[PDB]
Amino acid sequence: LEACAF
Amino acid sequence: YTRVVWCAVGPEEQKKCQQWSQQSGQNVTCATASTTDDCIVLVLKGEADALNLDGGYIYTAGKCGLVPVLAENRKSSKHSSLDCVLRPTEGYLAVAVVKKANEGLTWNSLKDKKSCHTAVDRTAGWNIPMGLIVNQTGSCAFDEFFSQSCAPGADPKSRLCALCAGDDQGLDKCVPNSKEKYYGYTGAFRCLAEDVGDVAFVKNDTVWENTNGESTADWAKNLKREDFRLLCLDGTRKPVTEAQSCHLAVAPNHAVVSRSDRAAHVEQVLLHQQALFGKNGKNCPDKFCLFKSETKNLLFNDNTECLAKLGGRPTYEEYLGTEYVTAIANLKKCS
Ligand SMILES: *[C@@H]1O[C@H](CO)[C@@H](O[C@@H]2O[C@H](CO)[C@@H](O)[C@H](O)[C@H]2NC(C)=O)[C@H](O)[C@H]1NC(C)=O
Ligand SMILES: *[C@@H]1O[C@H](CO)[C@@H](O[C@@H]2O[C@H](CO)[C@@H](O)[C@H](O)[C@H]2NC(C)=O)[C@H](O)[C@H]1NC(C)=O
Ligand SMILES: *[C@@H]1O[C@H](CO)[C@@H](O)[C@H](O)[C@H]1NC(C)=O
Ligand SMILES: OCCC[C@H](O)CO
Ligand SMILES: [Fe+3]
Ligand SMILES: [Zn+2]
Ligand SMILES: [Zn+2]
Image (cartoon, rainbow over all chains, first blue to last red; front, top):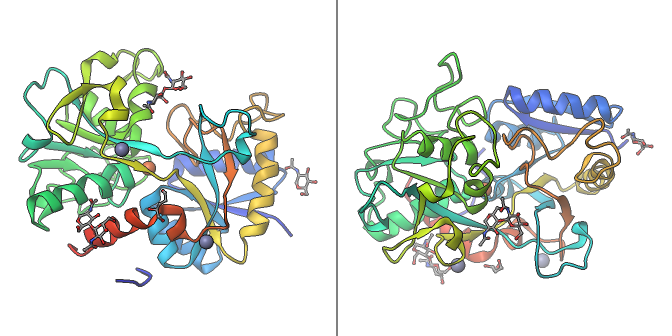
């Protein structure tokens, strides 16, 4: 449910 | 050492930014990208310092570690004694709008109709209405709900882009920047006005600012508010004067983000820049107006009175609010 999309 | 690099999204924001740069004596300079997501990346790489973002894009930028710096603040009511810069922001109303003559269309009969969205991942244009729909239908298949749509940023050959129109040459169909005719609050409301779509997901202010002579743009100069209705979540339809009892959600104001290591310098430069070019700034309207762009909402919404200081040095989660963040998170389980 969490992480930078780049 | 406070030269601030602004990021402009698409060619029209770039031109406005260049005019700001010139007037600021290069205290602000410009970097440009084709999409908001690309401008976010320039910021993460340190090739740009900042830009103003819708709440859905603040979620993206904040999961990558960018932080809010100052918020757009528009015309108030309560708390009227305070300076704009020190006034608490109050959020805007997300609404679903249809033509009054499209009788018998309600929230409960939207399936298989045509839709108009500001852009994929934006608050009023996408996160709120598609989150509600997926929930209500028990289905992640949000790209098969409407028969056709314009939702900039989606696959250009999908039905989600079928209604978008591209630029006046017809190029850049469905790109998420102002060159797309139906991009943004104003593009999505135009998409409804010209009857390309049955419904438009925008905010309450957009309806008022582009009707009854408030805009003189050709597609809008002749629109009348009485020709529109809001769709309420209980199945009823209301006049656009009732947005307070007929909206989809209250959304967090657009806000400037930057790297945490540049936040302080970005804040100071902006506070001084708006003293020069903001609403009653000392060189606006004479030399440059930072919060005007002929209703096209370039860099900032044209209805911005000032950029306001935030209370409590909030994280992007505290800015957006726990419930909105969770709605976004839930909706993103789908794709
Ligand atoms: C929906 O948006 C409109 C447009 O911003 C709001 O109307 C403005 O409100 C201010 C003060 O309340 C007036 O001084 C302006 O003249 C209004 N604009 C126009 C063009 O009328 C309206 O109040 C909003 N509705 C709700 C319930 O928030
Ligand atoms: C769609 O449904 C989900 C699931 O109910 C909603 O998430 C709940 O949100 C409330 C209010 O924030 C919380 O108390 C619950 O913890 C959430 N549940 C889960 C499983 O995460 C979500 O808000 C809904 N989306 C929208 C836009 O309404
Ligand atoms: C540029 O910034 C400098 C230092 O902050 C300030 O002295 C000057 O007035 C600014 N010029 C303009 C026009 O923004
Ligand atoms: O917008 C008011 C803040 C409430 C939020 O949902 C909790 O962080
Ligand atoms: Fe928005
Ligand atoms: Zn409400
Ligand atoms: Zn905090």
